[PDB]
Image (cartoon, rainbow over all chains, first blue to last red; front, side, top):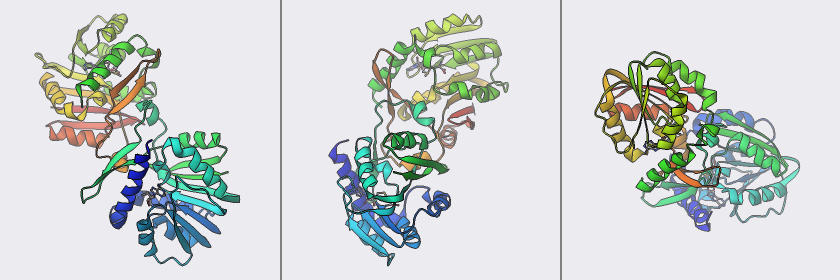
Length: 213
Length: 213
Ligand SMILES: C[S@+](CC[C@H](N)C(=O)[O-])C[C@H]1O[C@@H](n2cnc3c(N)ncnc32)[C@H](O)[C@@H]1O
Ligand SMILES: C[S@+](CC[C@H](N)C(=O)[O-])C[C@H]1O[C@@H](n2cnc3c(N)ncnc32)[C@H](O)[C@@H]1O
């Protein structure tokens, strides 16, 4: 995965910031009540770190559950959008998550629709930084798109193309990372990295994960 | 879709023909009884045409249900393997299905796991020839892989990846066409081309279609 794909994906979200909520993540609206049952399970409490907060759709929920939220995003434009919710207990910080080392620790870490934008060759290092961010007794939780277990094997592709072309309505076009991972695949891969994981398809096409370091 | 992908796909199966039954189609063995409930619904009868017969897994069944089977495959190697079943009422013919205009008509046309190897730019001409091959009162039935209705939109790719990369036993690597199409997508496209279609997911990961001209 070339650095061009990382930058073109960032630039994409930097440019999509104005119009983002006009479209949102496809069918996330269908899946939100199922994901919310997991989000409110009680692990999102105290000092909470959110990764890739975007326009702050999840940040609102976390704000309601946490004492304080630290919300990180690569796009200052996303941050400005998120500011319009006026959430008293949220601090925003701009941060390239592919070049990030936490300095403190938090009770819980959350991200929605971020991991699928992390290519396999960046997976492990992202997850090492996530590890250091988790306070003792803390949890990592995330939401993402998913596949049924067997699709990967039916497809049987030895060089999966991670890239997807997206095009705004102004006409400028971008390639982004889009890696659909099954609950089984993420569990295998994060177990190998030392996490204990409960990863579940909560609604067709969507997963929710709880990971303990 | 370049002619080189088409050729690569056919050479992949030519080379695979001797070891094909050793791996077969992933999870088809799980889905076979469900698919058989449809195959045995009574439309496979009289003179049937089979497209992309391979090693004759389905030809065996077609042979038991029909009077006569004409089985077409691009690979003589595949045809040689299929001959080992010693089916009395079956005639094999080598035929490149992307360069094919039937001269005869049949009571039924069947194919299993062929349509997913027909790229979008070849789909219409393929169905045009299939239309020529169906006798009045006849049907086309087919088995293939499937996706959940919503995946396509969740991915949201404007240049969808038509291709996957396979590796043989001996290490030889080949790109092939692998287009997963939902029942609704297939129904909508085939209806636009004048077919009435009953397309159903009969087992997770697998669909069965009955199409009428
Ligand atoms: C649409 S997805 C996240 C969805 C939305 N932010 C949410 O949490 O529901 C992309 C988000 O990740 C952010 N992002 C993309 N590349 C990044 C990077 N390299 N470093 C940090 N954030 C990045 C984008 O700014 C965008 O907000
Ligand atoms: C994975 S399938 C095998 C079929 C298997 N017997 C079945 O029906 O379940 C692909 C089959 O299509 C054939 N094929 C690939 N390209 C072709 C082409 N251009 N024309 C005719 N047959 C082709 C291959 O020879 C192979 O037998």
